[PDB]
């Protein structure tokens, strides 16, 4: 058995929860500008190499569009604060093959 079991900080669940909120947002702005009825996952890996297909506005100073995990807890809060303003401009959809029709009806469980 364990003697001095050391869990995780209580505030930790915060810094982690914040990164998630920002992660989704980027998806909302991206999918929203596309004109779809659902959120789309922003391909950071791709956007990183090619920052033209989709632009990002409403960002702070001395910053650079990147994963919401690379930003310090401090910065993270900012994004969420001035998020309502953050916008996304789609210049062109990345190059990728479409997916064949399979099963409709997205659910959780």
Image (tube, grey):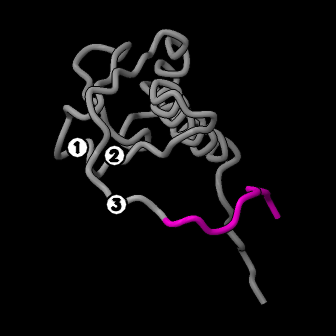
> Which portion, as a residue range, is magenta?
100-109
Q: Is residue 48 left or right of residue 59?
A: left
Q: Nearer the observer, disc 2 or disc 3?
A: 3
- Give whichever of 35, 44 is nearer the camera: 35
Q: Is 108 included in the stretch rendered in magenta?
A: yes
Q: Look at 29% across and 52% down and name the residue there.
A: 45
Dot 3 or dot 1: first in sequence order is 1
Q: Residue furthest right?
A: 109
Q: Which residue is mark 2?
A: 44
Q: Is residue 93 left or right of residue 6?
A: left
Q: Which mark is residue 84?
A: none
Residue 90 to residue 81: above or below: below
**Which quadrant: the N terminus?**
bottom right
Q: Nearer the observer, disc 3 or disc 1?
A: 3
Q: Is residue 15 left or right of residue 99?
A: right
Crowd rating for badge 1 (residues with CA inside 10 Å; few <14, some 14–19, many 20+) = few
| Element assignment for label 1 | helix
- Distance CA(mark 3)–CA(mark 1): 20 Å
Q: Look at 58% across and 38% down and name the residue there.
A: 39
Task: Give percent across and percent down for residue 55.
Answer: 28, 25
Q: Which residue is mark 3?
A: 97
- Distance CA(mark 2)–CA(mark 3): 18 Å
Q: Which mark is residue 48?
A: 1
Task: Give percent across and percent down for residue 26.
Answer: 47, 33
Crowd rating for badge 3 (residues with CA inside 10 Å; few <14, some 14–19, many 20+) = few
- Give whichever of 3, 81 is nearer the camera: 81
Q: Is 52 included in the stretch rendered in magenta?
A: no
Dot 2 or dot 3: first in sequence order is 2
Task: Give percent across and percent down for residue 12.
Answer: 62, 46
Crowd rating for badge 2 (residues with CA inside 10 Å; few <14, some 14–19, many 20+) = some
Q: Residue furthest front?
A: 101
């Amino acid at each position: 058995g364990s003697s001095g079991s050391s869990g995780m900080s209580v505030d930790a669940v915060e810094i982690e929860t914040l990164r998630k909120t920002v992660e989704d947002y980027f998806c909302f702005c991206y999918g929203k500008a596309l004109g779809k009825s659902t959120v789309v996952p922003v391909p950071y890996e791709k956007m990183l190499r090619d920052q033209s297909a989709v632009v990002v506005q409403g960002l702070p100073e001395g910053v650079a569009f990147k994963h919401p995990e690379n930003y310090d807890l401090a910065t993270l809060k900012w994004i969420l604060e001035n998020k309502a303003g953050i916008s996304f401009i789609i210049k062109r959809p990345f190059l990728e093959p479409k997916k064949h029709v399979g099963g409709s009806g997205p659910s959780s469980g």
